[PDB]
């Protein structure tokens, strides 16, 4: 029954039901910043991220709470991670290296081939000879061992590391936890639950945090809700991710796919799209 509309098109509100699991993500560039036997996640007074995650699992006793992690953790951190799993019926640790993301990969050569083509499809004298030279040289130097977009991002240790594998986890959604249904409630670790979430609805079963502080309105990737794996709004984002080798900060493939899926163009009403897409919940402090 319940439909909403944006940009002159109607969308079903789809249910994100009460067995949808919650996923948090922590990618750790420096596991040596932690004492012996402690979980290599930040947990200070300023950033009580681990307590927030355990707080959520406590409150949502009948959902699976996931912690999607990566970094060169020691055996000792692996142990402390395993102890965390055992202290909480409904928490599982999901190590990036253990997840098959291969279904979303693309070869670096395929990507260079595209970029290089699009460059050559320009007039005899408005072409970028400098760029084409660097691209063709970068193409030649790819080993067949390392001709994987995914494998290149698994090596990185910065924010692009985090964001790349966040996008892929969102496409896997509930599958990443392979009771739990097929969707996923992706939350930032700084978000604090204060009660149960219950049943959530989203346009075409996707929603995103909109930060409404300082009389400003910004869409943020810090919280994303999906009703199903391989959501098509996220596959649009995968297409953007596949068109670049080293995407620049704030390229935001995720956000670009979602906006493209809903025909949110740079000329449409920003505030209306925020109203329409927003995930807000009385029981989450965002």
Image (spheres, rainbow, N blue to C red):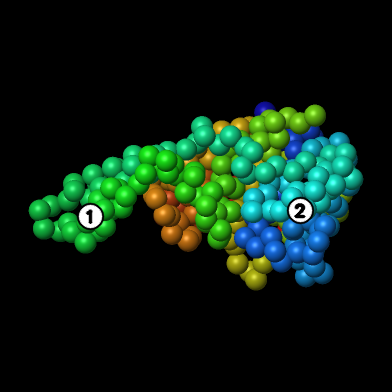
In the foreground, 265 or 28: 28
Residue 214 sits above or below residue 92 on the image? below
Q: Left or right: 196 with respect to 246? A: right
Q: Residue at x 52, y 34 (%)?
A: 102
Q: Which residue is mark 2?
A: 77
Mark 1 vs 2, N-terminal side: 2
Quadrant location of the N terminus in the rendered image = top right
Point out residue 29 in the picture as x, y percentages from the top left corner: 62, 60
Point out residue 83 in the picture as x, y percentages from the top left corner: 85, 47
**10 Å neighbourhood of mark 2: few (<14), some, or many (≥20)?**
many
Q: Residue at x 53, y 40 (%)?
A: 234
Point out residue 249 in the picture as x, y percentages from the top left corner: 48, 61
**10 Å neighbourhood of mark 1: few (<14), some, or many (≥20)?**
some
- Mark 1 vs mark 2: give the one in front: 2
Q: Residue at x 13, y 52 (%)?
A: 123
Q: CA distance from mark 1 to mark 2?
A: 45 Å
- Tell me whether the residue at label 1 lies in contact with that at label 2, contact meaning CB atoms closer than 8 angstroms: no
Quadrant location of the C terminus in the rendered image = bottom right
Q: Residue at x 31, y 52 (%)?
A: 138
Is residue 216 at all visible to an observer of this figure?
yes
Q: Which residue is mark 1?
A: 132
| SS class, disc 1 | helix
Point out residue 140 in the picture as x, y percentages from the top left corner: 28, 48
In the foreground, 220 or 89: 89
Is residue 11 at all visible to an observer of this figure?
no
């Amino acid at each position: 029954s319940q439909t909403v509309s944006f940009a002159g098109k109607e969308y079903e509100l789809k249910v994100i039901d009460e067995k949808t699991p919650i996923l948090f993500q922590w990618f750790e560039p420096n596991p040596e910043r932690y004492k012996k036997d402690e979980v290599p996640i930040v947990n200070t007074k300023q950033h009580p991220y681990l307590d927030n995650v355990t707080n959520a699992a406590r409150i949502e006793s009948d959902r699976m709470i996931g912690i999607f992690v990566d970094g060169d953790f020691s055996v000792n951190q692996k142990t402390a991670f395993s102890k965390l799993e055992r202290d909480f019926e409904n928490v599982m640790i999901i190590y990036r290296e253990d997840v098959d993301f291969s279904m979303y990969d693309r070869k670096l050569s395929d990507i260079y081939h595209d970029i290089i083509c699009e460059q050559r499809l320009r007039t005899e004298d408005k072409r970028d000879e400098y760029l084409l030279n660097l691209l063709e040289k970068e193409l030649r130097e790819i080993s067949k061992a390392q001709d994987s977009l995914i494998s290149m991002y698994a090596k990185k240790r910065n924010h692009a590391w985090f964001d790349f594998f966040r996008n892929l986890a969102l496409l896997k959604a509930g599958e990443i936890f392979r009771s739990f249904g097929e969707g996923c409630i992706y939350l930032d670790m700084d978000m604090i639950l204060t009660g149960k979430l219950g049943t959530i609805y989203a346009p075409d079963g996707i929603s995103m945090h909109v930060d409404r502080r300082n009389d400003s309105v910004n869409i943020e990737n810090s919280a994303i809700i999906v009703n199903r794996s391989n959501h098509p709004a996220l596959l649009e984002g995968l297409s953007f991710m596949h068109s670049k080798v080293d995407a620049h900060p704030y390229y935001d493939g995720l956000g670009k796919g979602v906006k493209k899926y809903f025909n949110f163009t740079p000329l449409h009403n920003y505030n209306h799209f925020c109203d329409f897409i927003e995930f807000n919940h009385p029981n989450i402090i965002m």
